[PDB]
Image (cartoon, rainbow, N blue to C red):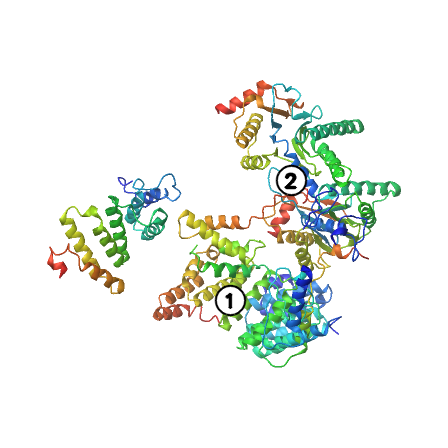
Amino acid sequence: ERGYSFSLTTFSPSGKLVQIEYALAAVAGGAPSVGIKAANGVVLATEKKQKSILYDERSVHKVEPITKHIGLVYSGMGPDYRVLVHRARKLAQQYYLVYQEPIPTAQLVQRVASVMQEYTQSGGVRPFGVSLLICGWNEGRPYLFQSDPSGAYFAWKATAMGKNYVNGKTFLEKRYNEDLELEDAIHTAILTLKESFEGQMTEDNIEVGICNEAGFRRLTPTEVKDYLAAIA
Amino acid sequence: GADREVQRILLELLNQMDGFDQNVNVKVIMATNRADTLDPALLRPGRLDRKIEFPLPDRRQKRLIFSTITSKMNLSDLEDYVARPDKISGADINSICQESGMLAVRENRYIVLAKDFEKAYKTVIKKDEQEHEFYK
Amino acid sequence: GSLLAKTGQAAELGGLLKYVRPFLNSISKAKAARLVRSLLDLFLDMEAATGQEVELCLECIEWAKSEKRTFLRQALEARLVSLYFDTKRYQEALHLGSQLLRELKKMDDKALLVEVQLLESKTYHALSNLPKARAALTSARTTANAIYCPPKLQATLDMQSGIIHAAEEKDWKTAYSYFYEAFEGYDSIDSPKAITSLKYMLLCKIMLNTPEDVQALVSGKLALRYAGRQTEALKCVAQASKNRSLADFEKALTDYRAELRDDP
Amino acid sequence: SSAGFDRHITIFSPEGRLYQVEYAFKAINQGGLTSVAVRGKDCAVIVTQKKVPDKLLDSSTVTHLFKITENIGCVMTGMTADSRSQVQRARYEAANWKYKYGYEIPVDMLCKRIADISQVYTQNAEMRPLGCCMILIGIDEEQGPQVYKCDPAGYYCGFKATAAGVKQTESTSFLEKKVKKKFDWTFEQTVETAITCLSTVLSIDFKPSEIEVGVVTVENPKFRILTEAEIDAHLVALAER
Amino acid sequence: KEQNGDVKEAASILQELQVETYGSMEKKERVEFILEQMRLCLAVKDYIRTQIISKKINTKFFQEENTEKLKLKYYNLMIQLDQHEGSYLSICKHYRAIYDTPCIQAESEKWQQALKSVVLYVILAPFDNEQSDLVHRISGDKKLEEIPKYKD
Amino acid sequence: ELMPGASGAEVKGVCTEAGMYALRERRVHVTQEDFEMAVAKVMQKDSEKNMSIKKLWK
């Protein structure tokens, strides 16, 4: 089994590629991220806690927008996340140029899954060690998707990945209800983050973003602090 | 030869536990840290009827551990320390308490309190990442 | 209706209950159930005249059955079981709760299922049917370890578990731990349940013939916000125990006669 | 449990670890020098230990900190050849940015671009991922001074203060002890705090002629390299106080 | 502070200076102010702190240095602690130890008074095997014949 | 029917666990729910927690 956990172009005699599984394992080691599809929108949160308070928390962002109505968060590597952001933005605006219409989130997820799976085609290029959570609002329906390093993309009413993803998934199973509203979805997401935050989340310690019929936007530290106080 | 002999030992264990000549009033107990690597022939009823999981103490269990190990401790907020979310086992709790006592011995005070107990708590559950931030 | 409810006298509640007759079926099920349960809670908690409360509960039950509001019917049935248990209509409460649980197993609703199971365990304990109460409590715990179980429900379940363990009269450490969990969950959510939980925790400490931990716990940071007559009386009982003066024990019981003897 | 995986950059180890990147991070400390940057309200000061093997060496060419653009300064450590290749690449990127977009590069944008370059470098097996750690400093309008750090992993981050070198851990701890006091850090205070950190992390009480300093302020947008007079004045003023 | 009237604050202030962390040279006779802390805390009458000092003095030898003068002071402090404690066999043992040292063996009146006090301490103690051992070991003492009443 | 692909040894273990459940409540008879939770306990096995891994194949 060792001799086949070394290349991306060789099938293990029993199952499938082992480098893909190792990339997923790297994904599982990332900062926890939680996505929730509410009735009127979608909300994705992540933890930004890092030692050495010297770090400028506003300098980099784990949550970024792709277009006026689609955003994303990541779990796993950072630079790969930025590369995925660049590819998604370029591809979304290419679709916009061809069609003069805001990008359907499903198509963006499909095409970004294709571009990340492209890196898995041959050896010498490692697969992205990042899993994507894509939030969007299109045609009167909030869409939340997960994109894999393997290129697999699927839907999620509410999911949690990264570190401690299994317990967060269980928590989401317990708390999620299909009739959830946006603010209550944010409350549930922040509660999920707190369930494994380990160190008293602050306004900048967590980065959250919400998408609805008014597009997608990352919540400022002010509203994050307000919601944190509301949850307490 | 080595792997063959080890598997012979395992097979003899299986055939003795639930083989031809059944045993009477012979209960076996086997402990492992990685159950998922055990042979399925050993993990079936008739051989290992009950596979009891011993998870890390959860909140209430942590309080029980702290109480039952602090019975021999000195008088000394243990409840808050229990409330702190840390994936630590009963061995870690016994450590924490023992280290608190050791530090109190160092400082020559016969009742531990927040300072040395907290210092021992930090010493025990280090979990210092030393991890390059590009992984997160 | 809101003005009447804020005013809230028995005749006014009686009139209002049928005065919102078209209101019940004019809105969605969730809000209607929430409002009627709020009216029921206020009516039961302010005026304690059991004769009218029980008959109003039965009238609401037949109302819901006629209106075919299944979820609402289950909610009011659970509330009426709680009322019966409070008024110690043991057989009525237990029989109705079992009848409810018979049809509530198949329904996906579990929070109300956990409420019903906990009420059944409470009644079963009040009947000295300790083993069957323990079985019902275990079933409730199992069915709650898979559902939201809000901090109140978690606190209530831990309180009942501590009560059961104490009544078993064999292990107090687990009883102590369950009481501690019930208190901490009841912190900053419901006050009377929190004080009762702290009361039982101190009692459990006393039964461990360790009153010193009681006098340490009363000064504990979380006890101060709930310090008062209850904790002082329990501390007095603890002192009577530690110095082993049953004359002091009886004096403390005479003091309890108003405070902690009518509490089962 | 994972032995052969620490050979190729593009190879994922079990538990999803890339050992080659960590080895490059360790290779950064092969220079043995130390750099540290501190940012104030409107100032940013970088300071680097200077190591002269011989007076034969020309001190004007043995500098370890350089200037990317007229307002953006760079201080870095690691492999010296990797250092110089990285600064050349960064200057190319900044000039191309200016050519294509007609205005100066912000510190964060330059750091992000070179971080993307380094990530592409570490993603494909054709490249040795440029084992040198860089810190860029510069003034951006509406956001004041900016100090950013980029590493061979392609990870860039903004810092209220930062450090690099063999003594990175202790310097970062001292910088944390300094930043927890929440002080405005005027220019002289920034310089003296950085100098104190370097001295206490080296425990040498260096002579004035063994260090280099660069400073960027809003009133002095040009990345000035501190000559001997200014650094001597700063260090003696600190020493008497 | 002894000239001011402060005792509790006084004892605290001279208590915060500990000797366990003190590792530069053995405590020896130089820093005997452990007994000074005992004395100040006795003036505060906070006997538990004195007991803990006595217990934790083990790191600096279980007993004070021999052939010295701080004995009588430390032993009188321990005796007063035990007198309030109510224990007797410990104080009798300490008094016998004081009688043993050559330092007290200069002036006969002190021998008489000390051993008379030891006899009275050992009398009002309860009965056990250790008590019998001590009493019949000291029955053959040749330094009590000068005063026959206490021997009687 | 509650045993998809369960060995005979697992069936005997299920019978034993149902008896154990009855014994816990200090009874002698066993009920249907006893067998149901015995099936749940005996046939319990750890699955693939990671949905990402489980969704590699279509």
User: Type of residue at label 1?
Assistant: Ala
What residue is pinned by disc 2? A57
Position of residue C158 measured from the top left corner of the image (x, y, whole percent): 56, 65
Q: Residue at 62%, 54% (x, y): give it.
A: A195
User: Type of residue at label 2?
Assistant: Glu
Residue closer to the observer: D205 or E65: E65
Position of residue E78 measured from the top left corner of the image (x, y, whole percent): 27, 51
Residue closer to the observer: D152 or A161: D152
Position of residue D182 measured from the top left corner of the image (x, y, whole percent): 55, 35
Image height check: is D213 above or below E30? above
Residue closer to the observer: E145 or C122: E145
Few, some or many residues within 10 Å of mark 2 (<14, 14–19, 20+): some
Provide the secondary structure element on which disc 2 rests.
Answer: loop
| Quarter of the rendering containing residue E32 | top left
Whether residue B38 is visible, yes or no, is: no
Whether residue A210 is visible, yes or no, is: yes
Q: Residue at 61%, 72% (x, y): give it.
A: C80
Q: Chain of mark 1?
A: C
Few, some or many residues within 10 Å of mark 1 (<14, 14–19, 20+): many
What residue is pinned by disc 1? C175
Q: Chain of mark 2?
A: A
Q: Residue at 16%, 55% (x, y): give it.
A: E116
Q: Residue at 57%, 55% (x, y): give it.
A: B88
Q: Report, in whole angstroms, how far the alpha carbon at label 2 lies from the one at label 1.
A: 46 Å
Provide the secondary structure element on which disc 1 rests.
Answer: helix
On the rendered structure, is D6 left or right of D162? Answer: right
Q: Which mark is residue B18?
A: none
On the rendered structure, is E69 left or right of C254? Answer: left
Image height check: is C222 above or below E23? below
Image height check: is D221 above or below C6? above
